[PDB]
Length: 232
Ligand SMILES: [Cl-]
Image (cartoon, rainbow, N blue to C red; front, side, top):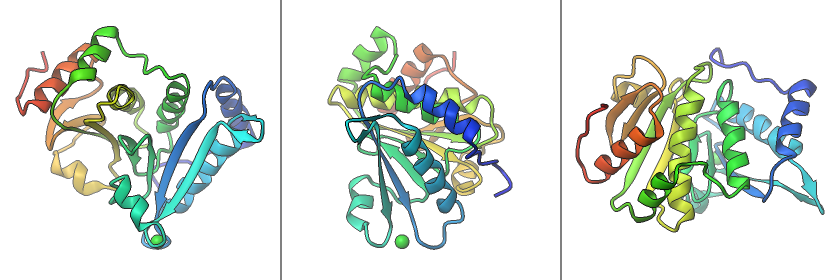
């Protein structure tokens, strides 16, 4: 593709391996692809195979456990994780995912998500964690991004951590999806996205840019209750 430069060099592998060397607990990642009709799937697999390879190995166990699924032979898995589009890179039960290759600047958010899940720590504020525990109502976060986008990683990280925090507390009502615009132009145009990152929640554009955690919590709570709040 023309919108991202996949770096599988030894230099990157070295840098990645060094960061992942600090992983605490193992993390499973689920990659959904299609044998055909998916231009970026091959690259996504190369990228994710690289991540798995560079993750630490402790007692024959790779700290990053890669699972790869194809639309055809893995139909039930797609249904289980509620994956309709490919390529998709998901964690948990699919509540944290990238719909579209997490290349370019997204590598930063992908690494951080892996690290935080590994550390059993979302890194969110206590107030946020407490709110997510009891949050009622489903929340579908779509953070529209592109691989080259410099600030997207921060927005993606935030939404993903919200989904993770809720999920780890046994309240998986949040689906945080990082939607790569080039592979999913319809979603980007559904929200009239002019600049990335842009964030939609429950089918409506909610924020343009990277929001503050505390503010995002308000957006999430309001979305859950089907209400509109001020970016304020
Ligand atoms: Cl397939």
